[PDB]
Image (cartoon, rainbow, N blue to C red; front, side, top):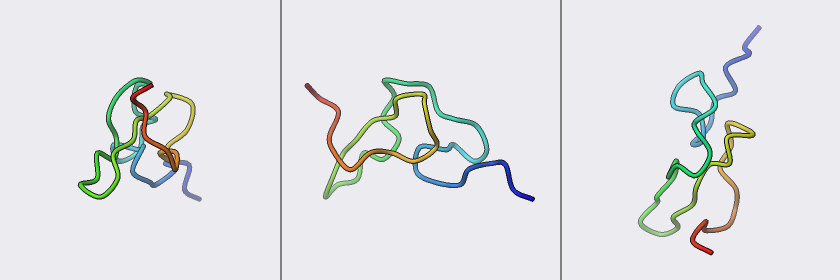
Length: 46
């Protein structure tokens, strides 16, 4: 049982706040939509 939702959008076990850089990968920067714990596959700067 793991309801933490591991991922880049998940600080560790809590859906990061929307409009907050979760990934910010040097090769690809994105943002969390406070909807899931998995950052999208697109940059959030528009």
